[PDB]
Image (cartoon, helix red, strand yellow):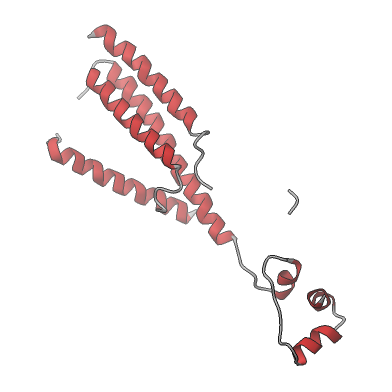
Length: 30
Length: 110
Length: 33
């Protein structure tokens, strides 16, 4: 149950962050 | 910049348009009816392909950086014309290259 | 001797299947509401 409003875009920002980190880690590891 | 670089910039503008398009379609429509499923589905396929592309492209470039080794051995240096090379004006080194009939060094001297 | 970035082109296809899906979604969403 997300509170939406600001919290939603907070979660979105963290999602983008962890996405870039995992993709970058994958590429570097390859 | 190396974050935005692997994907073309026009691709980033395009994905922004894709985002606002999906958002506005969602607006026009916690399960919601049917259409929300085809929207979320097509966006899923899309975002999967994009993350895969960023991963692969960044992998390729980071591979290129590690696969490219500058001049190291001397023989390797001799066959390339990109990097110019030389010696002292008068010395045992220059006279070595000159008087030496050894293949690699002969080429270098030439 | 004899013999970049992500493709602005090759990637675009995905953007087209996406746009198509979204359009179909326009149809499906609109007819019900």
